[PDB]
Amino acid sequence: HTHWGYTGHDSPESWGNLSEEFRLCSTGKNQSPVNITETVSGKLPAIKVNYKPSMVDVENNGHTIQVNYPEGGNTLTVNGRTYTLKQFHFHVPSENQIKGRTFPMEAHFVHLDENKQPLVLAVLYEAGKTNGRLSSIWNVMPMTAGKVKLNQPFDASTLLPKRLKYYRFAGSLTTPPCTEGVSWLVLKTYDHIDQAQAEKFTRAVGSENNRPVQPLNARVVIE
Amino acid sequence: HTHWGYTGHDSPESWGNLSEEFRLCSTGKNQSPVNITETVSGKLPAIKVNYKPSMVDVENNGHTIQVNYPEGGNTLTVNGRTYTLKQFHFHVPSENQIKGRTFPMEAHFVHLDENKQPLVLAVLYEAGKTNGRLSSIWNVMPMTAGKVKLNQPFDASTLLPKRLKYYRFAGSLTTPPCTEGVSWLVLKTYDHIDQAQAEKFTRAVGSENNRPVQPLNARVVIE
Ligand SMILES: [Zn+2]
Ligand SMILES: [Zn+2]
Image 1: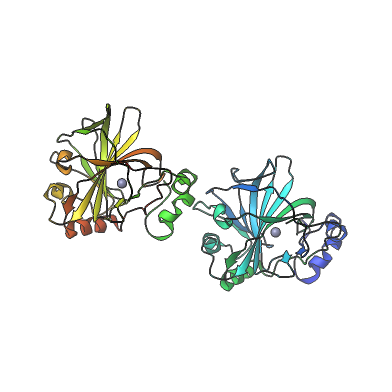
Image 2: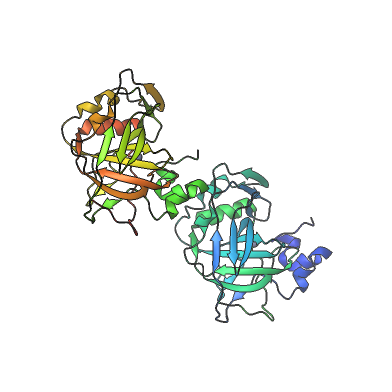
């Protein structure tokens, strides 16, 4: 596709101008990420997560470190609707902010339902002790653009907190073409990582990979 | 099968995350072993054992030292039903506990009825005099992963106490996939072993091989 990045001439502020296909990045009114400040308290449906030990591959596509799921079986159910986990990746530092706070890292679990409707479940990481559950992925992390098949099974359920309360809002993909119509569920409970793990990620990717926050406009964030 | 153990990243706490087939190890509500503290006094049916000198082979499968029975003929009858002894193995230290007490060793005599329903008869060993009845097995014990044919016939009846009174509860296999629906009969009368016999076992297996005790939950132990 058309080349884009986080630094230089093809930075986020230039995404909508580097290709007609990326126009929504600059003209969209329902863009992600956002800075969650004010919220409307509401009775949100409980999410049911059904992740399991699976055979996955880890790739460095030059924009992030992504863990792919070629086989089905890992799903998230919310309000009677089932979404299949396609992949999960990270951003260092975080893209979304809570009351203006940027976190060391943020993970995005990308799902699709039967009708190709996208849903992103987000996990924020605070600076703290080493994350032992991410060690498997970090150990085989391609330091240059490429894909490697994780030989041992990986269970993404280990990456989710016990309590699944979340913030909900409508948004878009945070990378070109910035497609809208994406459901965003940001978990309110944070996980942790150390400086070394975050630094290694930036090394592999080549730069910080977070898109600046976008205005909420007509949207409200439910909590 | 997927690798699992008692030490490192594949320890008992992570079994349920190693493969989807091991999921019951972490989600099961009727898991073994257990710490027998409170019990209900009941009229339990008598156990009838009909073991005989048989041709067996001793095996070191990396998880325990197991004595395999290629042919039937060694049976245990309780409450009208007959179970055939398939094999017996050991755990050092013991898996099950009696009022918080861990024993130097525990033997598991695994049986299966006509319909493949599992029944485990357990014998606990106290530290004491050398066990002369186990010498035949201990002397040929493979110190590395392998199987050796026992040249002389072995009669498992010599490994059972005179008094066959027992504790009765429903549980599971104490190793992956942690299958439930297993009937557990733990003998009240203990046998003995020397410290040397126990340490030789540990040396052969590579580590202690006892799964931590599990919550009884809705279960009651009868005696
Ligand atoms: Zn992302
Ligand atoms: Zn056992």
